[PDB]
Image (tube, coloured by chain):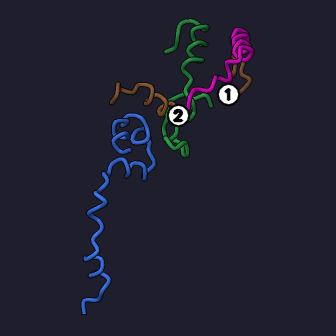
Chain colours: A blue, B green, C brown
Amino acid sequence: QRDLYLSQSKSPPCGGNPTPEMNTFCRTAIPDFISTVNFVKKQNDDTPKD
Amino acid sequence: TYLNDPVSQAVFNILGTPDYSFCMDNEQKNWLPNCNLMYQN
Amino acid sequence: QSGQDSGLTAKSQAQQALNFIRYASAQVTPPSLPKLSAYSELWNQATAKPNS
C-alpha cells in the first residue's frame, strides 16, 4: 500500500493537502514486525531485577 | 484575460468550471485558506 | 444604471440583455465536475502502466 501511495505521489493521498496522520503514514516507513517480538526480553522486563 | 467570443466563453465555462472539492483537502473535510480557482459554488 | 452593490449586476441596457442571456441559458449554475478524490482514484487506475 505504501509503495502504491509513493507511486501516486502527485495525486492524493500523499499529494494535495493530506491530513496530518495521512502525511505521517506517507512519510514514515514500516518496520519489520518479527523483530519486535522477543519473549526473553519481555519476561525480563516484567520480572523485578531483585 | 478572457476568450474573444461569448459562445466560446460559455463552452469554456461548461468545460472548465472546477468542483468545489478542488478548493478543499483530499479528505473533503476542511477548506483551504487561499484558492484562486473559481469553483461552481 | 447601478442597481445592486453586490452580485452579478448590469449597468447598461445592453448589459441587461446580456445578463438575461446568462440567466436564461442556465449559465449561472455550472455543471458539477468530478470530485478531486474520486477523480484522482479513478485516473490513477486509468493511466496505469502496463503490468507494473
Question: Image point 54% across, 45% down: which residue?
Answer: B30
Left/right placement of residue C31 relative to residue A50 reads right
Give the percent coordinates (x, y) of residue C28. 68, 22
Q: Secondary structure at mark 2?
A: helix
Are the residues at dot 2 and dot 1 in contact (C-beta closer than 8 Å)?
no
Question: Image point 51% across, 33% down: which residue?
Answer: C36
Q: Which mark is residue B22?
A: none
Left/right placement of residue B25 relative to residue B41 reads left
Question: Image point 71% across, 18% down: which residue?
Answer: C26
Q: Is residue B26 above or below residue A43?
A: above
Q: Nearer the viewer, residue B6 or B23?
A: B23
Q: Is residue A44 above or below residue A6?
A: below
Question: Image point 55% across, 45% down: which residue?
Answer: B29
Chain letter of disc 1 in the image: C
Give the percent coordinates (x, y) of residue C23. 73, 17
Residue picked out by circle 2: C38
The magenta stretch spans which residues?
C13-38
Quadrant including the N terminus of chain C = top right
| Mark 2 / mark 1, whichever is N-terminal | 1
Give the percent coordinates (x, y) of residue C8. 67, 23
Q: Is residue A1 above or below residue C39?
A: below
**Amino acid type indicated by mark 2:** Ala
Check disc 2: other Cα within 10 Å, few if <14, some if 14-19, many if 20+. Answer: few
**Amino acid type indicated by mark 1:** Gly
Residue C20 within the segment the image draws in magenta: yes
Q: Are marks 2 and 1 on the same chain?
A: yes
Residue picked out by circle 1: C7
Quadrant including the C terminus of chain C = top left
Q: Quadrant of residue C31?
A: top right
Residue C26 within the segment the image draws in magenta: yes
